[PDB]
Image: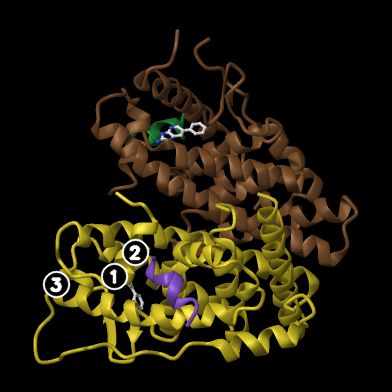
Chain colours: A purple, B green, C yellow, D brown
Amino acid sequence: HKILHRLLQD
Amino acid sequence: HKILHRLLQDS
Amino acid sequence: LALSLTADQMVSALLDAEPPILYSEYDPTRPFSEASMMGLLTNLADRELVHMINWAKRVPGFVDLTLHDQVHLLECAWLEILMIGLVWRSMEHPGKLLFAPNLLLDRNQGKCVEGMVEIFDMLLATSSRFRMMNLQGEEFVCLKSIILLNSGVYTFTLKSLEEKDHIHRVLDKITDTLIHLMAKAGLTLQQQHQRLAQLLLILSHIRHMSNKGMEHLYSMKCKNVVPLSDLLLEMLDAHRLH
Amino acid sequence: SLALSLTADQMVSALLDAEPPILYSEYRPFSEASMMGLLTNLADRELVHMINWAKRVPGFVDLTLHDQVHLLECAWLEILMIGLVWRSMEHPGKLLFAPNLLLDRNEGMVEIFDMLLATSSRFRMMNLQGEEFVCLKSIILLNSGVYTFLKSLEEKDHIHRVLDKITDTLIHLMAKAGLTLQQQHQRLAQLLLILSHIRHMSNKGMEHLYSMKCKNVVPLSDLLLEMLDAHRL
Ligand SMILES: Cn1c(N)nc2ncc(-c3ccccc3)cc21
Ligand SMILES: Cn1c(N)nc2ncc(-c3ccccc3)cc21
């Protein structure tokens, strides 16, 4: 679960 | 450095 | 949609999405070390990335894409994006790099970071170029948006070719926008496409500054010179580097 | 001076006229060492030729030798790659390194291979024209190393003037092919932006060529070695 991926949903 | 130098003069 | 945006709406959005200039943790009580300075840049970048992500989302067309794709574009362009910003804000600062309002360095100062100077020279060079052409803000954000869509599009089953094509359509609008701008700037037709060429050619050197930037970072990493954020680690990773 | 007096069509005819020959490779299965041998053997020979084409790139002989050296030291691998890409176009899923050496993606060079193939997929999807390709190729030569440059300011000035010409020439080409103004600009943009992807493949290959170097797995010519020397120094 890459960091960037989650940051791109917040 | 130098081979290229000499090719660019070759005629 | 981004394709029904006009030129002037295209420009308004981008200027409106622009990130803030962030300050460095600059501690003027000690002299720089290699480790310290690098710390400062990696701390700054780390914080710019978070804002960057939010900027990308406001780049027209960009939210139309799957997360995996957004992830990829960003992983490809992040350092180009940081460097083109740095160059831009360094514009009016001849001989210096304005990483932050409190971190304005010259080629003499990056001295203590092994291998940084070459990249410093390049960036100051790009800045003198933008200065000499008189790069405008409206043109800068266009360039910056181009870099984000472009850099990783080549490196993109059936939903793939629609996504590609989508990005190409969007890049075409920004091209239309760059031209709009120059026309409005009172440029002749000839000067428009000459200018458009000069700026797009500048991206080549920015891709190039990035690649050298990346490899230098990997070596600070591989030397345990500076701790890198879990985000930095991951973005440097993407470049599967060595 | 003479480069700034050429016409759109004289520019084009001079560049098609300087176009290098498609050289051949060496004529069982491949070892790692054997494969890269052919590539670097090929590349070396192609270098000798590329130097002669550069001298016939209008504007190029106007410069000093330091500067041709520097331009060629920066551009060389980009030049090679856009040739392979251009030659590979009409062979979907393959790289035509030479007529006898036509490979598919079937250590580390695979990522590079995938990029070159994508570049060729692009050129294909755009239907790049030959006249367009030789222009792009000259752009690469004059562009790549000018940033990293009143003896000097004039020379840059010169190269940038030559570059606008090649760009005028690219536009001629597309107006001639009957595209609208909007489409000339879009198109011009699309082709310049590929150069960014080419500069990127080249920076990557340079590093891969640097490990294949440190490895002594593959002899490299004294030229090939010096040209790789320039990218570290
Ligand atoms: C030159 N450089 C390298 N080698 N690694 C770097 N990481 C980040 C930056 C950066 C961070 C914030 C603003 C401007 C530049 C610069 C870097
Ligand atoms: C990726 N790569 C490495 N590492 N070393 C290389 N040497 C030559 C080429 C090459 C030569 C002619 C056409 C296209 C590529 C590519 C190389």
Q: Could you tell me if the residues under marks 2 and 1 are in contact, i.e. CB atoms within 8 Å?
A: yes
**Front residue of this view, candidates D151 and D187:** D187
Residue that numbered label 3 is attached to: C35
Mark carried by residue C230: 1
Residue that numbered label 2 is attached to: C234
Please give the name of the residue rendered at 36% of the width and 52% of the height, measured from the top-left corner. C240
Percent position (x, y) of residue D78? Answer: 51, 44
Q: Callout 2 environment at 10 Å: few (<14), some (14 to 19), or many (20+)?
A: some
Label 1, secondary structure: give it. helix
Q: Callout 1 environment at 10 Å: few (<14), some (14 to 19), or many (20+)?
A: few
Percent position (x, y) of residue D193? Answer: 61, 58
Please give the name of the residue rendered at 61% of the width and 51% of the height, measured from the top-left corner. D139
Q: Residue furthest left?
A: C30
Q: Residue furthest right?
A: D178
Amino acid bearing label 3: Ala
**Can I make out residue D40 in this image?**
yes
The residues tagged by marks 2 and 1 sit, at their Cα atoms, a distance apart of 6 Å
Amino acid bearing label 1: Asp
Please give the name of the residue rendered at 15% of the width and 66% of the height, measured from the top-left corner. C225
Left-right relation of C158 to C48: right
